[PDB]
Image 1 (tube, rainbow over the protein chains, first blue to last red):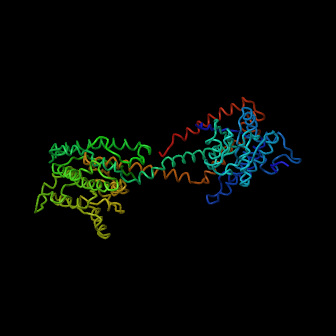
Image 2 (image 1 turned 30 degrees about the vertical axis):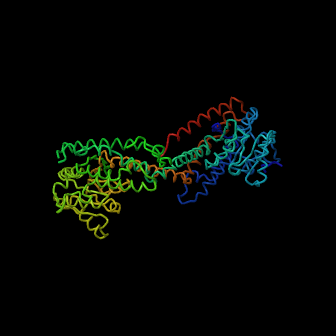
Image 3 (image 1 turned 135 degrees about the horizontal axis):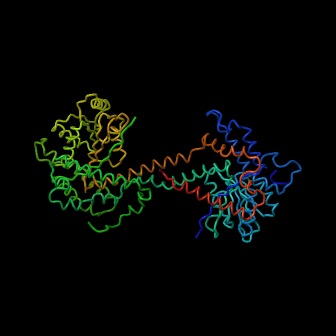
Length: 5
Length: 324
Length: 308
């Protein structure tokens, strides 16, 4: 999903 | 002609969420904050507090559990929970409006992860180089951003990762999301755009968290930059003390007063008067000599390296100014 | 305790009627080298030879053989008034002794100290001497003879070479540099035999300089070398300071910066407190304007510092 994970 | 770069420090505050985590970090080790530990303790405990405060000053979501609980959604709060993200939101909006492209540098690759989600949430086309990116892949990211008529607008990079001497002159604005302890790592990041090939005025925006740790970090790195520039300009002072005498120098020493020596049919100046003496005449000598001494010392001690340095063409002796 | 700074005074001296003849003879016997004829590889050796002879002439013509009146060679008044520096020295010492001062006399040439020895005998001045011929034991024995309380000695003759050996002569207060070393740090090391911790009086240094001759031009060249050494010293400090990692206090001041104000905050901080949501152009133009002001203010603070 999101890159910050 | 390459236009000198504009460098502007953007002093920024913190969101309420940042204040919470900033306090939470100081509270976890508040006895180290008060400086209560012995002078023997390692730098580790203080350095850890420093890095967590940098993570707090960059974005709260760098800490686990910070971002609001499940389900996790990319949203506007990804921007409005960090003081830099709010300033960046409008700064990028104004950068894109005037037809300018921007490189964005950061110290932490997990922050570029946050900026990646921001770029898609805002519709920005981009490239990214972490330093975990291979050699061939970061080549394509360079050329993609440099392509004539490129689609990309923002370039995400970590401060050190690019290498040396890469060319990103197609962009005109550089945004340092956070600074480096080494002022040369950041100046190398600015010069990715500010180098030969750039036609437009390069502007560098250095995000700084005011009234926090990043403000004092700024002054420590500013001194390091100033101290660096002082070593550099004296790099030729090593040779000047080392340098032996020229043929031009030796010739000038011998010729000094040589004509008056050849003219003197009797004796030279001081001895022409008497040559026996009156303590009035000796006290007149010492007073005149002390005057000439103070003039000589004050004349030279105010000089710098640019006045005492001998060019290499000095030893390229050709002819006499006027003959002897 | 208080150690009075040294008064460094160049005393410019002329040349005797005899000296001018030799200075001319030196210049005439190699007038082609003075003009500048020859290549640099071969004429620098020719010029360096002229330099030493002119320094020898500025010191005393008797350094040349056959200059002094023929055999037998006796110490009379002609030993003094045939050299400009000796005449100035002769009246300076007479004043120095009357004011209750003792003097260390340095020189580059040991053969000048030999001339100075016969002068001291001619005037009755008790002296000792370290010229680097002397062995370690002998040097020690002479230092002790000069510093002893109630000493009989008044003059101490040294070669500038033998100055920087760690000897202490604080019982003397006057230093006379008959001639100067091309490296100022060697002459400056000679001064600190008297001007070091232990001296109670004002150290006065007289630097003999043959005016309007080669010794005057060298004096300005030594000041260049002296200043460049200071800049290298200053560069070393800036070099070391740049290499220093943050101290534990440097780390502490960075963490504590604003820590009290953050603990004091309940809402938002700084910019986010001011407006802190979506920002108009007026909000951004106010930040960038105030920020650019602080950047000029910050750079100006450090751009006015430099190896001082």
